[PDB]
Image: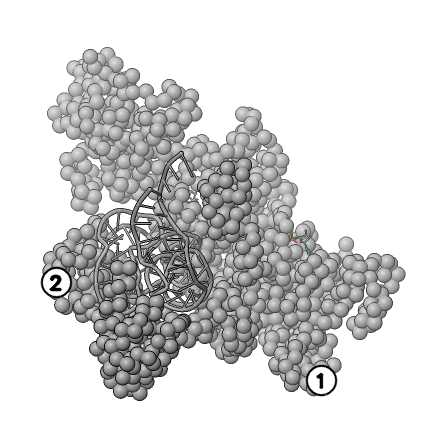
Amino acid sequence: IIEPSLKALASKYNCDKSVCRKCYARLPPRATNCRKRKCGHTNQLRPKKKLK
Amino acid sequence: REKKAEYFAKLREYLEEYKSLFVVGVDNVSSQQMHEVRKELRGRAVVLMGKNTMVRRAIRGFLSDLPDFEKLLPFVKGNVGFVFTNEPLTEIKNVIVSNRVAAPARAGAVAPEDIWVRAVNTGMEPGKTSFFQALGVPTKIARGTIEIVSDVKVVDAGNKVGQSEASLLNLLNISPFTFGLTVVQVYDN
Amino acid sequence: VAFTVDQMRSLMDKVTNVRNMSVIAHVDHGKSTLTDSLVQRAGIISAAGITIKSTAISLYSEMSDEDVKEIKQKTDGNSFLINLIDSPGHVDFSSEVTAALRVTDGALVVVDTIEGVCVQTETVLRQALGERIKPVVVINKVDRALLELQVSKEDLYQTFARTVESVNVIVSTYADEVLGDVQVYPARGTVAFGSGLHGWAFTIRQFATRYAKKFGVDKAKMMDRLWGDSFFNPKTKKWTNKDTDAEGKPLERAFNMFILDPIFRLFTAIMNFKKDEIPVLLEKLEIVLKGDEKDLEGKALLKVVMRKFLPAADALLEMIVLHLPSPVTAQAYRAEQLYEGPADDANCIAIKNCDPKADLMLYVSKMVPTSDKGRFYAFGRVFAGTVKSGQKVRIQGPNYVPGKKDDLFIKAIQRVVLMMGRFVEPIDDCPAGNIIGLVGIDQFLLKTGTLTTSETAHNMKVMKFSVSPVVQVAVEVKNANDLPKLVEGLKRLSKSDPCVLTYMSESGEHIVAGTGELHLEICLQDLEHDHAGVPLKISPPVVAYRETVESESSQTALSKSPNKHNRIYLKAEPIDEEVSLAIENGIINPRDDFKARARIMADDYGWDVTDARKIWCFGPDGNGPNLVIDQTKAVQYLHEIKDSVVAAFQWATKEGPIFGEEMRSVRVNILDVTLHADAIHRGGGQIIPTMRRATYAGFLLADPKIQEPVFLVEIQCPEQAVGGIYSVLNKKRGQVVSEEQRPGTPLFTVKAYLPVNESFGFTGELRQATGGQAFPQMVFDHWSTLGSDPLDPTSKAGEIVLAARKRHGMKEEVPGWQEYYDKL
Amino acid sequence: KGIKVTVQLKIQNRQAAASVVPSASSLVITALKEPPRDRKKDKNVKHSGNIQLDEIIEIARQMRDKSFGRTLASVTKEILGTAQSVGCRVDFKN
RNA sequence: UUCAUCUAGACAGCCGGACGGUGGCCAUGGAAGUCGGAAUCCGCUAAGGAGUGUGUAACAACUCACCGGCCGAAUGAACUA
Ligand SMILES: CO[C@H]1[C@@H](O)[C@H](O)[C@H](OC[C@@]23C[C@@H]4[C@H](C)CC[C@H]4[C@@]4(C=O)C[C@@H]2C[C@H](C(C)C)[C@@]34C(=O)O)O[C@@H]1C
Ligand SMILES: Nc1nc2c(ncn2[C@@H]2O[C@H](COP(=O)(O)OP(=O)(O)O)[C@@H](O)[C@H]2O)c(=O)[nH]1
Ligand SMILES: [Mg+2]
């Protein structure tokens, strides 16, 4: 059981993110830079790898 | 700014020559459908859309080629373009209010009215059965072809269309999310 | 309720009252343990999820002649014997599934409401319909769809409406139109509901009965108005076929209020230990409890209440007699594709007009095991005849044709036995259309085979399976001496399993092939302690390719006698595929006439009659694809040394120079023949390590590689599953040959090419790619040429080659033609 | 007639076997050409063409789905040339 | 420290088009704007790239550029320390 608007909203707060390539942390997909200072606030990021 | 200045001189050319015109508005339309319109009258009704370079067409209304420009500036707002002609309007008005049909259920578009459809064998082999499974609509096999069992009123008026049900409504020849392409203002001489 | 052998034998005699089907479904839907409760409530008695080696539970129940007005067949009995043979759903163990279909007329399907209609359930449903068998939609585990999920009437009916239309799609596509309209409709009273682990099960028809006049009209018309677009108005007191009132408010569908509602209220009440409401409804259903029955509360509370409400074997056997088939109606147009060749033949007609007293016909698909005197019994179904304890009848082997003799053994059975659950007991007779177990034919038959009295009978349909052996493995012993026992054990595994294909290889190993790796390790397990009885030695099947040259050996290699006298110069050229292929084909034979063999090679596969007519060898063993020709003509001792030449030729062309394998499509050319005076110095005693050492150096200067074995893997599988296949073959150099499909059935039969060294677990990755939907039937095709040059350990086969020499315990890597060469 | 990438419309009426060819851009570049551009290149990649053709390729544009919605002679000067790298007609289209 | 277009009507923003040839030259077991090389065109207007990506086995579908609504003055891009 999933359904369009339902499996879509679920992903919006779990898969629809951007995995930082230095600290991995979750940022808005439509991001540009990290909000953590352990990485020196890097810009190198990559959207959270999809399912195949 | 290069092409902004040349657009002025060009649209200016057709307005300075012809007798009567149409400042036609249209939000919902399709590119491919749009050029079929200009081809609907490749001569008597040549279309020409506009924007803020049309806010200057009112400052070209300040240029005033003829005093009749008063009855034109109060129609600049919305996706409104042009329609140039020199033949009787009732005849060509017939064509523009005959140049109006539209698009289907673009997964997640506006759902304003009631979604009701009858129950008779669709006429195609059992294909999108996995969708009506997680969807739950009464439909049984009648000579291989999937047959509508219930007069399913799918989605209720006023919401956001779901990806799954819109695609099967496409197979049902359901096109009600747009209906565009008319006039915004009527003007002559 | 059975009494005795003869009493149970007398019910059998009536084939009109013989519901012979099988139970298939999927890995964990509750079919094996649910069939356990049906027998514990209506099985058999005469005067006394992995399906781990199953048999066929018989069983028999009671009905009425009034139930008989609804069955469209020629039945006149009321006592019915239903023989259900267990058949494991799965897919990596679907061996016994194809066997059951053929040796039965009907079949039951255990679908689910929660897990629903799975991928394998969909394709296993196809095997039964592609065989012309009838349906039984049993949506079980309904207690967890209302206990550990708990839905609404209209809404749960939609999980069931899904179960309906899902099993329904396999029907209208993966079935046969000769059966008529074999599309199971819940309302038509062809769909089963229930809970197997808690002994209760009801049917659509079951409540149409406990309602008919308690409604006002016939129960037939009413139960068809119970499912679908049908609503009752608790105000107008009428039946309106609309889901709202004269105002526009919600209605609880006719189904939801009459069947569902009661169950719904009973459900909760019993599951909520509220005996303050239990008796009230317990009364509306005429249910009584006494003593230690009411000592069980909540879960166990509903367990015994609903049993006494919805009867196990009863409800499913209600639609099994008035719907599920027997030989009478089934074989009527089942026998068409139950036999090949003459369908208008009188022996196949015996099966159409089921005559136990005519052309004796029977097909043993299984071989139920019990190690005594011989080894075990056979298991077949009689299609036209009565069997006896010592009857003399013929055997149509998988080869045998009515006009020949091979695979035809006509012997008399020592004794007959009828299957009761898992064990049997000594019977003496069984007529046309009934499944029996004939023993004493073990030490004769070669697995699945026919058994007919009439010798003019053609040949039946030899299984089907739709799987084929594709899991490859090799064996040995941890202890050298117990080696012989392990080998006679593969013979035993032959006679202990169906799809298991044990064979020998070009490695000196006993190969094992099967349905799955689980399957394999399962046969391996049942073997390791039983069939074998000793520590084996399993590992991926050792592969041997072929050491072949191609770029025409440029320089002439020099190899003279060990005294240094008789020198011969050879050049290694490539023999065309269509050419070397014909040697192994039986076209260009090593015992054929040269003038006509030269006309053949010159015109059809182009060459100059000179070297064509002057051929000498067919290495190795004079049947392989290695041909030697004499480029000379002025040799004083031509064929006076031809023998010593052909001799060392095969020995060397068999045990290879690169590492140690025979060669393929290589033409050795004896450019120059330089011999000595006296013939004594001109004997094989020199010509052997001369011609051998000649091809040795000639081989390592002919620029050779390895033409290895390629598979013609036929991956017949679903359409949207095709996505996964492309990517999987896109990896293992899968060279997809063709790709055609039947417009209607989404199943796309696809053939391709796959490297032998690229398939040690290949099947596994396919099913993981798109669910157990893909189907790999790897049938080895030909030898596809590579390109890496292994004389340097960077080449793909180069690593393989040195480790093969390292394997055999040889001279390390590849020793240069200079180490074994002759000159200044 | 036509090979590489198939765009053939087929309409059916229960047993009614009838087809209507849409003649893609592939079909026109080989339709006017002679035999070595019709066959003989099974084991060969098609990459040559320049020589002048003319106006009759305007009616060949009527074979390539007329849903472009504009002028005929005008759009011919586009399709054939930039996406059509064989039989360029006038070396002015790129 | 440098170039745009720039209230005339901006960019960030939300609102409507993402086209024909075209399932383009080939290339394909398969490739249709998105495995791929080579071409990078004009019919039309407000505009649409043989096309920015996702995803189809490929179709389809969504989306970006381009361009129409409104928000309505800057404020975007490129670099130094
Ligand atoms: C009907 O079942 C068939 C198919 O599964 C397929 O044709 C399979 O092929 C087996 C092999 C056949 C190859 C040719 C005939 C020449 C080389 C042979 C092999 C040796 O390496 C390659 C494949 C895999 C086997 C190696 C592992 C020893 C072969 C063999 O039988 O020796 O054979 C079985 C019996
Ligand atoms: N929740 C629930 N589980 C069930 C029910 N019936 C059987 N099972 C489970 O099914 C399992 C056995 O499945 P099996 O009979 O092996 O499935 P099969 O191989 O498809 O026939 C057991 O471990 C039970 O826990 C039921 O009615 N409800
Ligand atoms: Mg089981």
Task: Residue type at mark 2: give it.
Answer: Leu
Q: In which quarter of the image is the C terminus of chain C?
A: top left
In this figure, which residue is indicated by the disc labeled 1?
C235
- Judge by depth and name the residue closer to the eye, C800 or B180: B180
Quadrant of res C484: top right
Question: What residue is shown at x 45% (from left), y 69% (from top)?
Answer: B105
Question: What residue is shown at x 23% (from left), y 69% (from top)?
Answer: B10
Q: In which quarter of the image is the N terminus of chain C?
A: bottom right
User: Are there few (<14), some (14-19), or many (20+) residues within 10 Å of tag 1?
Assistant: few
Badge 1 residue CB within 8 Å of ligand 2: no
Same chain assignment for discs 1 and 2 = no
Q: Is residue B92 visible?
A: no
Measuring from the top left, give residue B15's x and y in whole percent: 25, 76
- Judge by depth and name the residue closer to the eye, C275 or C101: C275
Disc 2 chain ID: D
Quadrant of res C33: bottom right
Q: Can residue C241 be seen in this view?
A: yes
Question: What residue is shown at x 70% (from left), y 86% (from top)?
Answer: C236
Measuring from the top left, give residue E14's x and y in whole percent: 47, 62
Q: What element carries label 1?
A: loop
Badge 2 residue CB within 8 Å of ligand 1: no
Q: In this view, does C531 lie to the left or right of C624?
A: right
Q: Is residue C321 left or right of residue C465?
A: right
Mark 1 → mark 2, Cα distance in angstroms: 82 Å
In this figure, which residue is indicated by the disc labeled 2?
D53
In the displayed structure, would residue C762 be above or below residue C664?
below
Measuring from the top left, give residue C756's x and y in whole percent: 40, 39
Question: What residue is shown at x 87% (from left), y 63% (from top)?
Answer: C290
Disc 1 chain ID: C
In the displayed structure, would residue C260 be above or below residue E41?
below
